[PDB]
Image (cartoon, rainbow over the protein chains, first blue to last red):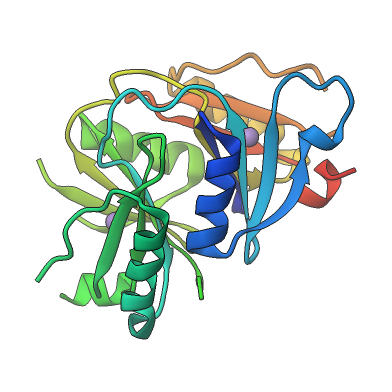
Length: 125
Length: 118
Ligand SMILES: [Mn+2]
Ligand SMILES: [Mn+2]
């Protein structure tokens, strides 16, 4: 049996900028940096978004953008606030459709989504 | 405030094969049916939509938590499907890494963040 999600891992060109994205958009909390170690060549950081473990490692960006995406849940009341946060970070986004979502990209062609709706709502529609 | 994970969406060339992988490896259950399908892995909403496979493989990955006592079983599930799988490192704090048919890397992992932080 699958107990739940363990972690999601993203490879990014610039660990510092990705840190600012995860902190700026999701209020991610940095819990680990391999840079606190002596002679570790590879560079990684671990973050928590609530109880979600996100790991980032420095490497190459995704070649192309695609519609593979990871979506986090927010409340409908915070939709404009979150669109603002994405704005202040200077991130590319998909246009807001006329549940609702904000889709944006980090600096390495990963797509993320902030979605106000639920599965139950989605299936009933 | 982020309330939690909403869903994860994968683009795949063949929804029937992806269905078999999700059900076969993760015990995913289908709740909605070129087009999209929806699954739950426990309370994790997964959406799959027909389209183009990732040009390239990378080490970006999604990892699911399993118990160490189930490790051999899960490795046999991935193998039974003919999925491209990294031979498990003889070990704990263990992982199984595999690609589906569309260059998405997945991981089954027996350890926790807390343990890893040690
Ligand atoms: Mn989505
Ligand atoms: Mn991993």
